[PDB]
Amino acid sequence: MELKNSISDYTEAEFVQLLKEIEKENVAATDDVLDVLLEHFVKITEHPDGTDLIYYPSDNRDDSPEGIVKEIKEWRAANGKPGFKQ
Amino acid sequence: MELKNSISDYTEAEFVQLLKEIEKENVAATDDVLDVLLEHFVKITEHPDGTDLIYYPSDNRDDSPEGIVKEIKEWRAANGKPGFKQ
Image 1 (cartoon, rainbow over the protein chains, first blue to last red):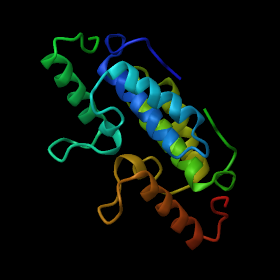
Image 2 (image 1 turned 90 degrees about the horizontal axis):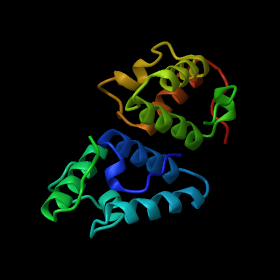
Image 3 (image 1 turned 180 degrees about the vertical axis):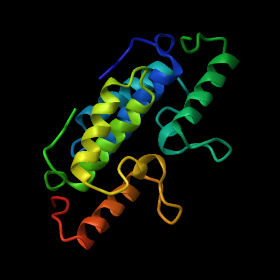
Image 4 (image 1 turned 45 degrees about the vertical axis):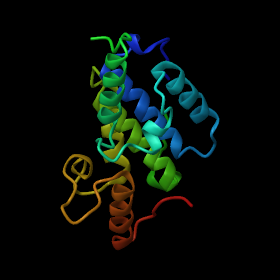
């Protein structure tokens, strides 16, 4: 599994791959890896809504991997924090 | 990555996890792993439509992981072949 130190080390596609890994662990028999992926996701995005970005997408936004990416990108830009790698 | 010998060794959820792995490789920089997952998917499902089950879902069916699972389950049952493990 890929786990990078911060949002800026990920390209959008690589971040989408972390989100697919999380999608895969949602149907895992156990939660061991899922909790690790979810803890990591929260630590690195630093988004106020945490895992809600995944389970409770806003009604005005695309409930999809790229949709989460967009959400993060915008929040970080509005706050003057480094975004995704190019 | 999990790769089992046949459809009957997979539970529906484990098969859904193979499908998520394939979803992840679609955004991979390279196709090396993707072609392996896709070759495997075709060999074990033995479904006439091959990878079209993924890229070109029928209009009358749910374009989702469980949707593919249902499709496979039905085709195998109509042909008297062993299905998923319980």
